[PDB]
Amino acid sequence: INVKEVRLSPTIEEHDFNTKLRNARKFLEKGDKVKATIRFKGRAITHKEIGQRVLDRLSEACADIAVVETAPKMDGRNMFLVLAPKND
Image (cartoon, rainbow, N blue to C red; front, side):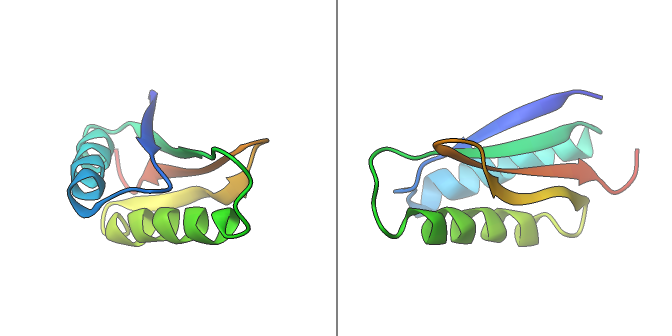
């Protein structure tokens, strides 16, 4: 019933990704929605592309238990995705 936040770095390394992925699946299994957010520092030309790619990886890795309620999108200097549990 909650919206739990999972924060991702644009420079995110493999173990931190898996740790965040574990946490997201844990929230979703508990019936809570997940807002996965990337807060961009600076204006790299490649930010939207990699933020998209990091969140798409999270979304596909949770497809077995979640639906995408809000597909990756910008909110100022942030990009976010909302996943909702398939069942509850």
